Image (tube, rainbow, N blue to C red; front, side, top):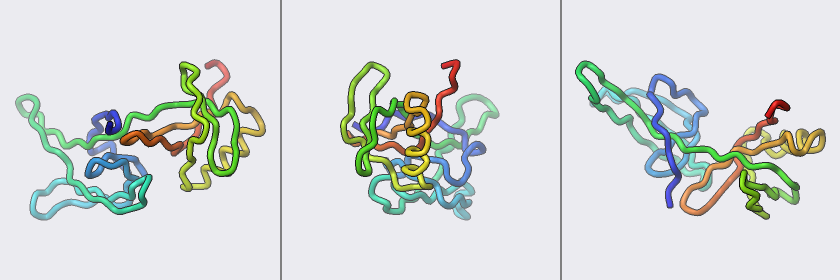
Length: 148
């Protein structure tokens, strides 16, 4: 099943954001304007396959004088990190479900940043997880604030 999504106004999209392009979660690497339509065009790199995809914004008119250009972004899940072993991690969902071999994307030194944070406080460490058509991958990390 394809990733759950949220709607993002185009003004709020910047390079590096993750969007659904052609049904695939992609890192945005170029934002341009279509000369034929005037809409924003997004070029991105598939998080899983590393292929390039392109998609233009969707224009809508939800109310008088309201014109809206939006894109879809993935809903990210947040898992705890229980262990790190050879490029993948053991992660736990909010409900205790254990994922034994969760891959970590090779992007912006994520693995090294995760390893450094894991070794100085394991359970303050969370991974942000994208889930597309059955497959999951950690694509970012967070150190959970103590108050949480």
